[PDB]
Each structure stands twice: as C-alpha cells, then as structure tokens.
Amino acid sequence: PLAKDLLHPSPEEEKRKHKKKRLVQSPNSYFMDVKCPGCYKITTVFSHAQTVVLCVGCSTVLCQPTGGKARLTEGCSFRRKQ
Amino acid sequence: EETRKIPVPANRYTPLKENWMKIFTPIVEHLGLQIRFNLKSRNVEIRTCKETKDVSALTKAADFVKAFILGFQVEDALALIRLDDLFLESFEITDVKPLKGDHLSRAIGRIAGKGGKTKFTIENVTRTRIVLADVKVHILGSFQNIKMARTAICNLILGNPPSKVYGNIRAVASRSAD
Amino acid sequence: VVADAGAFLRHAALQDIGKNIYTIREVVTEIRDKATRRRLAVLPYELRFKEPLPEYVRLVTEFSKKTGDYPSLSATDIQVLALTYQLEAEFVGVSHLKQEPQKVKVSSSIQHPETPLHISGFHLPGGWITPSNIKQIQQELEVRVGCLTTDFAMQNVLLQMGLHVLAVNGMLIREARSYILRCHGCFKTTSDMSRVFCSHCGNKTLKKVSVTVSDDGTLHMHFSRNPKVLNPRGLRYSLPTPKGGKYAINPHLTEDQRFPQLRLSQKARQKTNVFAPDYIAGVSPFVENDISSRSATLQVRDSTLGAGRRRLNPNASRKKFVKKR
Amino acid sequence: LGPQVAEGENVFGVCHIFASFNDTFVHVTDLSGKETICRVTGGMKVKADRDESSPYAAMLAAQDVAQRCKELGITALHIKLRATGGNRTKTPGPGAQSALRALARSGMKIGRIEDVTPIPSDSTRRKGGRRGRRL
Amino acid sequence: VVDPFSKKDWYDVKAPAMFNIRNIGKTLVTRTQGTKIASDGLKGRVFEVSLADLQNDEVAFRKFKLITEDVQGKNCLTNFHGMDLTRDKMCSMVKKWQTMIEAHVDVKTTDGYLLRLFCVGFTKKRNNQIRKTSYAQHQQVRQIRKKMMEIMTREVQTNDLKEVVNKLIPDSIGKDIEKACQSIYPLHDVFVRKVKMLKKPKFELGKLMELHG
RNA sequence: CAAGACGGACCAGAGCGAAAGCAUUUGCCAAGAAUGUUUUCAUUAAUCAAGAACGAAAGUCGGAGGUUCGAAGACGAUCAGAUACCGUCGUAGUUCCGACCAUAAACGAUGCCGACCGGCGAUGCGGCGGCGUUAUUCCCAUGACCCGCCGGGCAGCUUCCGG
Ligand SMILES: [Zn+2]
C-alpha cells in the first residue's frame, strides 16, 4: 500500500485478475487446433464453443458445450495456436 | 439381567468423553452396574450384574446419564443418583407461545439474561437446575420446585420483564414454606 | 524398587513386594495432597532416603538430551532415574545395559489422533466396565530392582536404556504405548500432554502422535496420514488491537504473556458434592450460584469452560443473537 | 389363576403409562393391547384434585397395578410412555417417571422402554391464542 | 364381585417361520359364551414385536406388526402385517448439517399383497471433509429419490412376502440403496423405515401352513 | 372408516422473488438471476409528475365447505368498590373459488443509478487451474471431498480511513 507501480505489474497479478479488470483487456479464451483420432483433418475449434462442432470429412463429434470451456471427446488431439 | 440403552447426540460426545470417569465411577462403585459406550450405535448401555446391591438402581443410573446427556453437569445428576424425590421435566419454548424467528431468539435471551444471570437467579430461588437447549427448556428439581421454575420460565417467555418475575417467584418461595 | 510420586499419589500399598525401597526427599516433600501425606505418617517405615552422587546424574543428563525427553522430564525425575541407575550399577552388573539408544522407525496410518481407542469404556462393534474390573483398569498391564513410576517420559528413556520397570501392579511391563505431542514446524517432541505451545519455536502447533516402546529398546511412532489434521482452515483471522488494563482478555498468542488477574469468587467456583455425609442436612440439593459478586457481572468464566467454542474456526457464522463472551 | 408358565420364563404385558398434565394413567394390557388387565388413575388414589398429577398418586397407582399384576400372573412389563401430544407438550411428565420407578421397585422385570407420544407431522392450531399459554 | 379373569383363557401367540424365535407371547381371550366365538374374537389383533425378540443377533431398533389369522387349540398363528423403525432411532438419525431424502412406492408382491414402502436416507460427511454442512443439491436429491424408488420397486415386485420379509430383517434393500447411490452423493443412514399393509388377498389356510411349517 | 386442516423435525444469519411472500412426491407450463462467450445490435441509457400491475392480516359481497382455533355472546369462579385477567361452550371468521379494499413497527425506523477510499476468511451459485482420497484399488471421463483463483450474491469479523 501507498507504493505500487501501476504501469508495470507482474504477469501473475494480471493473469490472476478478471479479464475486464486487466490494465488492458485481453480474453482468457483461445482457438485450439484439433485433430480427430480417425482422420488427419485439421480443425480450428474455439475453447468456449457453445455449438457442437463436427468434422467436415468424417462427421465425427469433436466437442460438447459445457458451462465454460467445451470439453473434447476422448482420443482427440489439440494444440493451442500461436 | 436387563439393560437400558440411551442415545447421545453429536454435541454431547466430547462432554461424555471428558467426564467419562466421573460418570462411570459412581454407577459401578456403590450401585454396582456394568456400563459401556457403544460407538457404533452411539449409546450408553447400563446393565445389571451379579454385584448389583438392590433393584431399581439401574433406573437411577439411567436418569443420571440421561440428565448428563440433556446438558446438566455431572454433579447435578449425581444428585439424581443420591436423592429419590427428584425429576426431570422439560418442554419446548414454543409450547406456550407461538414465536417465529427473531422473537423466539429474544425469548431465549430473557431466559438467560445478561451473563446468564436471570437463569441463575431462578436457580437460586426455585432450588432447581435449568438447561437451555436450542429451543428446549429442561428443569431438574422437586415437583413443587419444577412447578415454580416452569411458572417463572413461562412468565419470561410470554413477555414479562425479569424484575416482575423475580418479585413473583420470591413471593411464591416465601409462601411455599421454604 | 524405587518409588516415584505417582506411587504415593495413587496409593500404592507395594512395600511388601520390594526390599530396596529408596526415595528422594524432594519426591516426598513436594506432594500437596493431604490424604497421601496422612498416609505417609501411618505407613510402615521401611523406606530410606538416599542421594545420588552426580556422575550418574551427568550421564543420565547427556542421554536425556539424546533420547528427546530432556525438556519433558524435571530435575527430580532425573534424580530418581539416576537413583535407579546407580543402584542397578551397585548391585547388578553394569554390562547388561546398552547406551546411545536406537533409531525410531516411522509407520503411519489413516486413523485420526482423536480416535478413542484404548479407552476402557468405549467399544466399537465385549468391552464392559464391571465391578470386577475397576481395580484392574489402570493402563496396559503386562527381579530385585524396579520402579513405581507412572509418568511416560521416564518410562520411555528407561526402556530405551533397558532397565525392567514395574508399576503399582505386580508383574513387570514389557510394552508401553501412549501419546506424545510433536511440533510440525520444528519437529521437536514433548511428552507433556497438558501444554499447547512447544518449547523450541513457541508456536501453537503441537499435534498428537502415538508412540510405542518395547522392553528391548525400540521406539516407534505412528503418525496420521489424515489431511484433516494438517488443514490450515481457521488459522488466519483478523485480531483486535492489543488492549491493557484490569479487564482486557488478549487472544492468547504466547505461552508466557501476562494476563490480567480475573479470578472467580469462591462461591462461584464451588461444585456440589452429593456423597458427603452431611449433604442431606442441606436446604437445597445444589450449591447456590453467584449472582452478587463483581466477577459475576464481568462474566468471568472458568478456564476449562467453553472449550468447543474455541475449537470453532473464527471465520464462520455464529447465531444471530448470540455473543461469544 | 393365570398362565401356566415355568419359573424360568416370564409373562409379558404392556404398561401404557400416560401422564397428562392433570393426572396419570397406568393401563396394563395384552401384547396386542386389545384386552386390558389393570388401570388406576391419579384420582383413584388421592382424594384431591390438587394432588391428582402428583408423583405420590402416580407411585401409589404403580404399586396398586403391580400388586394386581402379581395376582393375575404377569411378572414383566414393556413400557409405552406418553404425553398429551398433538398440539400440546410432547415430553412425559414427572408423574410418568414416578410411576415407572415405583413399578420398577415393586419386583417387576422391565422390558422395553419406548415413547409413543402422538407427535403430529404438521399440526392444527394450538389451544391457546396468539398471546400465550400457562400463566 | 365376580372376577372377570376367571372366565378368560391364555392362548399362545407364535411368530411365522421367517424368524428364529417362534413363541412371541401369551394373549388373554374371553371364553365362548354361546353367541360370540372366542376364536373369532381374537382374530384381528396386531402385535408390536421388537426384532431382537424375534432373532438373537439382530438389532433392536426395528418393530414388526404381526397380525394373527388362525386358532389351532391354544395357538394363535400369526402373519406379517407391517414393519416400522423405533422412534428413538428415528429421533437420533435426524441431525442438522445434512440432507434428508424421502421416498415411497405403492408396490405389489407376486402373491397379491399390495404394500406401501417408505425409505429415508441422509447425506454423509466424508472422512476428510472440512466443511460443516453436507447439503445435496435438488437434482442430486431427485436422482437419489428416483434411484431408491426404482431399487425397492424391483426388489419387491419379483418376490412374495416370504423373501420380502426375509430381506427386510437385515434390510438388504437399504444396503443396496447405500451401495448404488454412491455415484451421486454418498448416503449415510439409509433404511426402509416403514412398511404398510395396503391390500391383502383372499385368506387361505395352506398359505399360512408354508408360512408357519 | 370419513372429514377438513396443516406440510414439523431436516430448516441454517442458507436460497429464491419487485415487494407482500415462498418448504410433502411427481408431471406439465411459461418465466429469471448469476456465470461463461475473440456472439449480435450500437447509445438503444438513469431517475421519474400523469398513468398502471402486484400488495400480509383484518374486513365486505356472491357460491362451496366447516377439523382445529376463535373476536362477539352465554355460563362458572374471583372481591371494601371489579364489570380486564382465568376455565367450559361457542357465532362471524379462520379453508377454497370468483369479485371488492389498498392498509402494517408493509423496518435497515436508512431512495435509486454511478465512482473512489483499509484488511481478513467462511458461505451460496457459476467458471478456471490443480498434486491426492473415494463410487469395495473403480478400465477412461464424470459425481463426493481437499487446495487455490475470478465474478455477482446473503451476511460476518477487524481497523485511530474519515465522519
Ligand atoms: Zn515448534
């Protein structure tokens, strides 16, 4: 208290903070690259997707909507993009 | 050989554990009764053995342990062990007046008073012991003394201030050949 | 056959079993109970007082600091232990005894430290207290020299050495299981079960750990692998500003802080005893309460009273219309 | 006159001890409860309405019932305690305790102590008003 | 003046074959005086027998209502009528910082006895729990209730009174409910607290013979 | 056996609702907060004279029903002067349906919206990150606990922030 550099805070405090209460707004979501266990097709899936996404050339369910992050089916592979 | 089993709540387990020697020693020493505490059924078990001196001692011990479980001190129920003409009468606080919520809590307050003082004053005049469970009142004493104590408590929990109750019970205790 | 204060405190009529009955003067002069002091003026006088030369006291001291029981014992306990050591050296050969005691081995279980095992009355699934078991329920019951000691720490160091010990019973004891307090900050163990602040780091952090000692000299400690024991739930809460005067009650943070004197009056701290021969002459079945003293208006309570209230965590919800003293 | 039982086994009755807040009833019945054996009130032992619910009347009642049951061969009793129940108070009074102790003294083996007080699930309105009850 | 108990008779009252102890007591019946038959007069009596008086090893907080049906020469043959927990046990089980879950079914046995079963269960505090309360949410409560109804419905429909009474004595239904409800919320003290007799078939004499011996 | 009533204990400084208020099971019906979103619109907002929905209990009209309780009223006791208290019975009412009434210590005796100024950990819901125990070691997720973090809540403790 009484001594806090408001311009340059630690990354731990900014990741701890609510997303609208950061020094500059930044979302907590991401676009993850998903590969089905069956086919080789690349799909891009939002981390908090509300809709059930299907593989285009396989017609296979990739994830289910949840209260927060969309959980993937078992066996699917994913990586966070950039 | 017959037995009596009485339950214990979760809030009286630790007082039972701390006061356990002071409970089981008078029951087994001069009354001659077997005693155990079943942890699975949460029951105090009192039994008659060959060493029991007389009949109805097991009833005396059952009243003693029941009074301890209801919230009385170990010596105040050892009074039930020694004396014959002592009883344990209890009632709910809503039995005389339908009280809801905060009103009810205030009624509990004016059985206790500040620091418990009011309660102790009744215990000084009526020669009883009063235990206040959460919505329950238990009186230990003689029959006429139980009547005086319940009159004081019922007067308190329908609105009377404590000073009027003190004056009334002191006049009654003067009239009761105490 | 040496007698500690626990022999006379528990009324051990054991002068017949022994012949080398040796006691210190300070074990017999520090007793304050009137009944056993009256008993000592009636009992047959076969005991004789004997004082140890201090080389044995020195050696008992350096392995008392090694066994981890030196803060637990007192000075007169060291005197009694040196007395039985020096008589075992004087009469029996000394080479029977091993020094520099063994290492303790760790074996933990899932049982809570507050599980009521080895309590005589309690029974899980028979365990009965009968009139034929009262004289026998003392502790876990199991040639020329012996002890009459009930304190556990002396027994712990004594069986760590290897002297046979006996109690107010007849037959000697081979195994001793009990409880100790262990600090989980500084890892210093105390045999004093009454204390709540440890002697080394001074924090309110001692927790119960069970111990078992064999006659061979093996100590082993049972810990509890229960996360409820080491849970920091109600430990951090806002404390009020420190207050002084004649009526302040501070939150008791250290073992030696100076509290103001707030004692109950003698009428307030009398409990009725019902088996007195003159009890029936009384006008009331119970002792009259204290409603007139100044300690009644200040709501002074006994130290043992209200223990479960202190055990609730302060960051919780009490009932709306109550105040916690 | 009574059951033809060997000395080892006991004859069981069921003693309903109902302590109302004006007197006390000691009602020994069959194990079924349909056929009765004995019953004396607080009022048939003391000749005063003031002392009708007193433990004196209850204990005299218990001795009278115990003697009558010794006459008819019943040696042991199960106990079914009772208060008025319903809207009223639920705890059996000191008269029920006095009757229980007095029949315990009078040579009776005691079976099961069980409380049947008619606790309502969800009651009707109390006999007193909003102002209160009992002085 | 004339003693009423001189004309009375003592009849044996005996339990069915499902229990180890048969003779559950004596009953007092006024003799047949021409108009009313003593055998017919005793035929509608309900006996409240604690289960520890019926089996040696079994716990004593369960009571069986047993109704008599036939008279066999100073023997009163008896049949199962109901079952209920002791009020002391019920008052001890209802603690504060937990949830009470109730269920009931109207279910019919294979031999025509229509019963009403009640089931009580409590949420359990775990052995490492720090929180004071163990409240279950409403959908969890509904799922537990639905599972209890399904379990006791399938356990009573497939049997008659013989196996139903034989599984009510150790409460196999209660232990099955406790084991099956762990995947939703851990249950603490589950019992079939009450069994009611709603409908009985036409009375048969042979049926009581295999129920007795 | 029937009748009407009421949903105890569980039941908490817990929850929901604009308030009055709301607690037996199941099903149906439309609502709603909060949370989550790198969704969409792009100032659409706040407070509001006039006006309008809801509004405990009591009470008034029509119908039904009346278990308990019960104003009035009838008795019995109680006393220099008692006509309120107490006990028994009991009508309107207390219950339901459809119309009225718009009042309470209808309370936090504290307008609503927005901003800033000390701290702490419990709880309710949602979300996130997790080493472990459990659904007799669960074959993988998922429920129950355990440790933190974020958002909106019901509240609490502490403080010489300032008043
Ligand atoms: Zn330490």
Image (spheres, coloured by chain):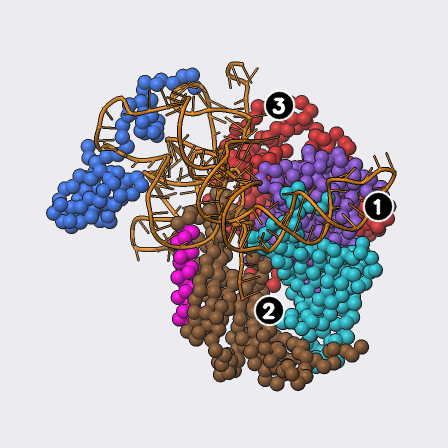
Chain colours: A blue, B purple, C red, D cyan, E brown, F orange
Compared to residue E69, the image places residue C65 above or below, namely above
Horizontal and vertical percent for residue E15? Answer: 57, 76
Q: Nearer the viewer, mark 1 or mark 3?
A: 1
Q: CA distance from mark 1 to mark 2?
A: 46 Å
Horizontal and vertical percent for residue C123? Answer: 59, 58
Residue range (magenta)? E140-159
Horizontal and vertical percent for residue D120? Answer: 58, 55
Q: Chain of mark 1?
A: B
State if disc 3 and disc 2 touch (CB < 8 Å): no
Determine which quarter of the picture holds residue C318. Answer: top right
Residue type marked 3: Lys
Residue position for label 1: B176
Residue sitting nearer the eye, C249 or C185:
C249
Residue position for label 3: C243
Residue at left offset 57%, top offset 76%? E68
Residue type marked 1: Ser
SS under mark 1: loop
